[PDB]
Length: 48
Length: 48
Image (cartoon, rainbow over all chains, first blue to last red; front, side):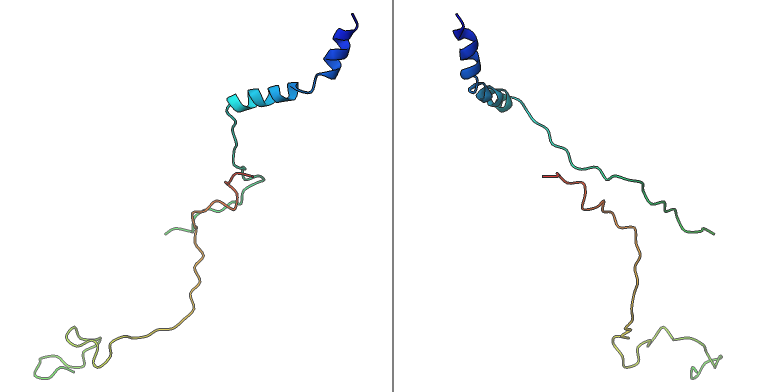
């Protein structure tokens, strides 16, 4: 009755396809890069 | 100087004939334009 563990270990590559099955149905999301770091400080010109 | 008038030695160009034989007063020079252009960066774009 040891065949259960051996077959679980051996025929365990097709589960990779399962990932695609969840990846195909699901909806992904990409985002643009945010400008990092501090920002330069610049005001107006002197007013009269 | 305006002929047949009550005032002479007038200053400034008259409004009658401001050209007097010229069409374009060509003015050549160098201009520097330091402006606040609306543009974020080469950022704000998908990384891939």
